[PDB]
Image (cartoon, coloured by chain):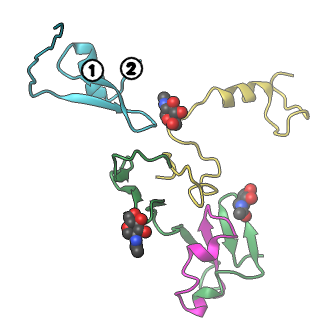
Chain colours: A cyan, B yellow, C green
Amino acid sequence: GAAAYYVGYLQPRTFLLKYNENGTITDAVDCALDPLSETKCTLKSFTVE
Amino acid sequence: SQILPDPSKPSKRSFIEDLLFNKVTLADAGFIKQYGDCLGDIAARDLICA
Amino acid sequence: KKFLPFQQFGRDIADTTDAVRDPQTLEILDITPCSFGGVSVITPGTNTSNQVAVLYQDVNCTEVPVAIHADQLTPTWRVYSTGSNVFQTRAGCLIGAE
Ligand SMILES: *[C@@H]1O[C@H](CO)[C@@H](O)[C@H](O)[C@H]1NC(C)=O
Ligand SMILES: *[C@@H]1O[C@H](CO)[C@@H](O)[C@H](O)[C@H]1NC(C)=O
Ligand SMILES: *[C@@H]1O[C@H](CO)[C@@H](O)[C@H](O)[C@H]1NC(C)=O
């Protein structure tokens, strides 16, 4: 009978979490993925001029 | 005429001064009657109330 | 305020208590500093006279008694809660000056 599942492993990381006006998480930034998201995490801004 | 004040506007700002006022934006909540709000207001969720 | 049912405590940027849900009555009651304001006293100098006026910061001249301790403080302080010499400025409500 056709079914599938996925197994992944967690890791101690730093995340930047965005909350909307409704109180739900709509986007996240991995602070240790790439230098762009790392700069977004340190500057605490999802955008950057 | 661009730099002199005109009687058409309620304020005495000129055309150049009106453009300078509109080109300044605030990253914080502005100083406009902010204690008229934050009292008896349902939407008391902003930076200048807090 | 629109409250998610799977939440109990609402906070602000400063991590203080902003909105809470009463477990008995399901209504949203906002935790606020109880009608605060700023007081600055304007005087012409004690060498001339003892008459003074009080300036309230940014508040209206209508909710000034429910902001100040109108029901708690002494009548000497309560002559400045309301009176005939009430003027509304952009900086706030001024009491004492004509
Ligand atoms: C937020 O909640 C309101 C009220 O239920 C809803 O209309 C809206 O679609 C929700 N999402 C956004 C992004 O505003
Ligand atoms: C008891 O608590 C429930 C919970 O919401 C409330 O609906 C009810 O009115 C309370 N009864 C009394 C007598 O306080
Ligand atoms: C408070 O003062 C402002 C500014 O004059 C006015 O627009 C507003 O109607 C006043 N509110 C009350 C309740 O008096």
Per the rendered image, the range of residues in magenta is C49-76
**In which quadrant of the rendered view does residue C85 lie?**
bottom right
Magenta stretch: residue C53 in it?
Answer: yes
In the rendered structure, the answer to whether residue C28 lies left or right of residue C80 reads left
Residue visible at 67% across and 65% down?
C60
- Disc 1 versus disc 2: distance between alpha carbons? 9 Å
Classify mark 1: helix, strand or loop.
helix
Mark 1 touching mark 2, by CB under 8 A? yes
Q: Is residue C53 visible?
A: yes
Check if mark 1 and mark 2 are on a common chain.
yes
The answer to which of A45 and C95 lies nearer the viewer is: A45
Q: Is residue C98 above or below residue B34?
A: below
Magenta stretch: residue A11 in it?
Answer: no
At label 1, the amino acid type is: Thr
| Residue, far top | A2
The residue where tag 2 is placed is: A48
The image shows residue C98 at horizontal and vertical percentages of 78, 76
| Residue, far front | A1
Q: Is residue B12 above or below residue A13?
A: below
**In which quadrant of the rendered view does residue C77 lie?**
bottom right
The image shows residue A49 at horizontal and vertical percentages of 41, 18
Q: Is residue C22 visible?
A: no
Of pointers 1 and 2, the one earlier in the residue sequence: 1
At label 2, the amino acid type is: Val
Instruction: Give the main secondary structure, helix, strand or loop, of the magenta stretch.
Output: loop
| Residue, far bottom | C75
In the rendered structure, the answer to whether residue B46 lies left or right of residue B2 reads left
Residue visible at 79% across and 25% down?
B15
The residue where tag 1 is placed is: A39
Q: Residues within 10 Å of mark 2 (few under 14, many from 20)?
A: few
Q: Residues within 10 Å of mark 1 (few under 14, many from 20)?
A: some
